[PDB]
Length: 387
Ligand SMILES: Nc1nc2c(ncn2[C@@H]2O[C@H](COP(=O)(O)OP(=O)(O)O)[C@@H](O)[C@H]2O)c(=O)[nH]1
Ligand SMILES: [Mg+2]
Image (cartoon, rainbow, N blue to C red):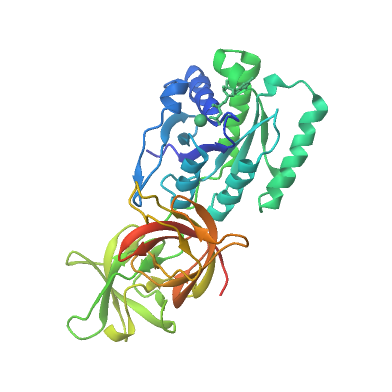
């Protein structure tokens, strides 16, 4: 502990070598700075996992650089990556997009990019692979344009992005000329990836779960400080639902123990000055003053479960009106489907425009669930906010 910890993963097109790279990384690193070398298969045969209520196939691996310690995840199929990205089951302070030099960019390449940004993947590094299969100076540089430029197409610094050329293969077999790229690749994670923003540091915030009124000199709302800190005296905004209202944090108690400040991650009951129980309700949230606005219309990438996992058994259509759980509650919304799209089948993902009846404190990257009679039928992340 203190050894900086970073969470990464290999994204990219199928067979482009995400997994093959993953391997090479631990190995190359084990041999060099000591550690544990992992076998392709132990990685290709991915166990499942259950997050937010779904089933993904994910392999978790570890390896260390000097200064840092990395947490790494590599998926089997695009979907796993899809689900994982949208849910966030596995976090990614950066991503190792994997591109083969024999195919150039591919649909999925795009997709994963598309998602990463949409989902708050802050940083992404690139390993041009299978370079062993290509000896064409000129060809390579074309790819970098194809890329640095596709990259910029989705709001990432294409012209400022690292691109490690290599052969995840040769390096896995033991061809030293090639290992250094894993090394070159590694170094980048260390220098290029800024240690993340911590939760406690991030802006203060708290989803209101319950609301009471004791004594009779101020009210008490409960819920988990999702982020930032809250110091008694720092005012707050109660955003969501009805017009926003202001107040001041008068008391912090966690199990009858009187305290002076709430930290991201703790469950607390905050005492507010001059606000009534009828002026506050679940769904709303305690947030540093001005750190978030409420909306009703938003663009989001969404996934509908299957029958096997427990989701709807049929498709749904426009004018569909399910519910959307946000941290603490459900809100009915109207669905708009991309041009072309006419019905969503269970097991599909679609960028879909939802329209809620009430306002909800929100910002891009938020994840929600979709439900029916309180049953979960899908999940999403607010890609972009509109209204
Ligand atoms: N020639 C060559 N083949 C490679 C290299 N890296 C991976 N491959 C091959 O590419 C295929 C797919 O690689 P893989 O890592 O499984 O891609 P994935 O489907 O994204 O996981 C495998 O059969 C590997 O042997 C490389 O550096 N050179
Ligand atoms: Mg694979």
